[PDB]
Every structure is written in structure tokens, then in C-alpha cells.
Image (cartoon, rainbow, N blue to C red; front, top):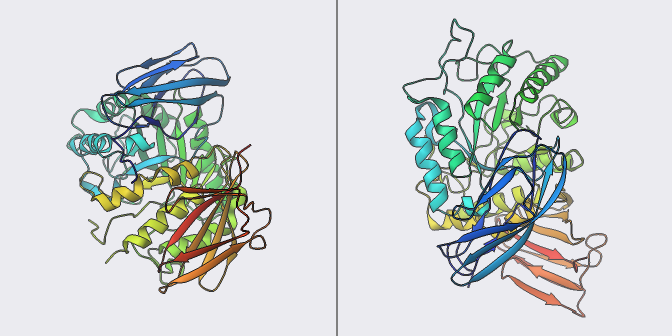
Length: 468
């Protein structure tokens, strides 16, 4: 049996590397599975940082650039977990893909302080925080339609009666990071105030409120690519001029090949496509509107070379478990494959579901420790789709330890069998295979073949090779 998130001896989970700018606030909750109560400690925690042994949160400010290797320890009644953490202080954020939640699908124009706080509380108690989900992102309509005559964005005080900073403080106390939303135009997609021409003011306000991520949309801006690049560069400079490490999420729907320029202008992730729908197949580029999961896979597949630490291709939100709720859907197996492939592609793992009231089956997917560990692998390679056959894909992701994760993904509505052998993919080591389906390792085998049986829509993942 697989141990649930709050049972058994401690297991310190991914990420095992974290980046932050020098002389900016640093917060990291150590994601840790296992029964509570739990106690944390550290060896070689650098000057500038402190660990709260009761809460598992590392916080402070580091002023010197470099890589610092810390040994973390988590202890409960049943045992101990010891794990290395590398802290890189420099100009590199999101050394692993960001994980978290975006508010739009659940709350739309009706987000409030209370509802953000409820969401944070639920992420603590449902296991998500302990599997590495850390970003809680406010989307459109937190602000009023017009800029204040004073030159500043106006917080909707009906929604946020104590301001955005209150929310940020609540989140930070619990190891979460706060995301906010604006647009590179006078008006956002929803028609409230954007940041064009006021980038410096807006960035300084975001930083004063304790914002940790900005999603920067491109509604109402000129199609022109040089203009887009310049508007994104301008906000990037504005963010770097503040006293915080603010993650910069570029959202111009993949129309100007952002994979070729977004990282260069300061982005840490960039949308590669139009919006994802809670649907398996829909060609949004043909009929307009939402794209299906399969369609976004086709778009992202050839973009692996552009992704890596501090610069991720963003295939949009995880629709896992939405079940056609909104505010028809996909099958459980389809949702599982969607999650699996987002993991393999080193995608942001940002849930768009209501995380306060998910069912066990949805959390079983979102909390999968092996798949998340693959997503968070420090090498940061986006899996290549090495084979796209009539019915199935083979995706391959090299890992930092020298092994290769291999995902066999059945697109079809009928069962399919895939026979992996030494000729399927180049440099695939059969001497040791870890199977994620049953958590078993086959070692020192004479067999150079693996029969993979897939249900409709199913993705099975394996890790090939011995560690260095």
C-alpha cells in the first residue's frame, strides 16, 4: 500500500533546489509527508536565514551570492528523513517549475480575502503544501476599473477590505507565495485597470504588498511582436528594480513565439498557447476559444529546447478534477495522464480547481510524489516526445542522476500495448527499471524488453537506469 501524505515516517519532498535574489525576502516551507506532530532542523543553514523547528519554514534574507548546501532533517514519532537542499542566491528564480493554484476558474469576479485565506488553509490540510504547492495566485478583478487620480491601481476594498498586504502576510506566515495579475495595456482582459505606462509604480506597489509573482497578460495590446517584447521587457525591469524576488509569468498566448524571447526579457515562464479547457480534445486555433489537453500537448511537444531552470514553457492550468463544474469534463484516467504529462514536460503545476472541496481521487493525482519528483528534477529538462505513433506517444525526460523517465501515453479510446525494447529509444538502460504504477524496481534483469499495457487514455511512467 502507498503511504498517505500524513502517515508514516517523515519524507522530505521536492523541490530540492531553490533560487532567490540577494537582499530580498526568502521564504521556504519544507514540504514534508508523514504523521504529525513533526519537528524540523537544519545543518549549515546560511547566515541570513533561520528555520522555525515547529512550522518547517525557513525565512530571512541572504545578501551574498552563491550556492549553499543545507542538510534538512524532519522527525516524528515513527522516524526521520534527512535531505539536502541547495539554496542558490543570484539572478535565477524558479530553478524548478512553479507549483500552486490560480483563482480564476473557481472564483472569477467574486474572489475575496476570506476565500483566498480559506484556499490557503485547505492547501495546508489537504496535503498540497507538503507536496510542494506554494503559489496562491490572485487573478483578474482584484483592482477597480480605473487607475486612481493619485496614479496608483485601486484595490477593490469590498473584496480585500484589509488590502492585499494582509493576504500576503497570512500566506507568508504559512510558507505560501502570493501571485497577482495585471496586463500590458490600459485595461485587463476583464476590463479593469492594467499597468501599461505605469510599470514602475505598479511593480513598487506589488513589492510593498509582498507579492511574489506577477502574471502579466496581453489583452488590448498591439499584435506587433517588437512592441510586445518591449512592453514585457519594461515590466521585467520594473520588477527587478523592486526589493523582492518576483516571479514573472508572461501571458501572450504563444502568438509571438515567446519561447524565443520571454526568458531574455526577464520572464520565468511563458504561455505557449491559448487557454486550456476542461476537455480532452478541442482545436481552439480552428474554432476559437478553449483548447483541449491533447491540443496543448501538440503545441508544447516541439518546444523542449527552450525550457529549463528559470524559464519554463507554460501549457496553462491543471484542470485535474474540475469534472465539468466550472463557474462535461474529462475522465479520471484522462486527468491522471494530463497531470503525468505536465510533470514530464517540466510544466508549471498550477491547479485551476477549487482546492477546498476536492475528492480523494483528485488529490491522489495532484499529490503523486513520484510524478512531482520528476517535474521538480533539478536538471529541469522538458521531456521530448520521441515517438508520436498512431495511438500512443513515448515521452522521454533525462534526469539529473543520469537516469531517464519514460512515459508511455495511450491517446486512444481503446486499450493499447506498448513493447519497450533496446531499440525503442536511444540510450535506454534496461539493467534497472522503476515502475511508478506499482512502485517496484526490477534490478539486474536479463530481459531487454518491457511490456506496457495501457487502458484507454492511460499514461504509465517508468524510470530507466542506475543512479550515478
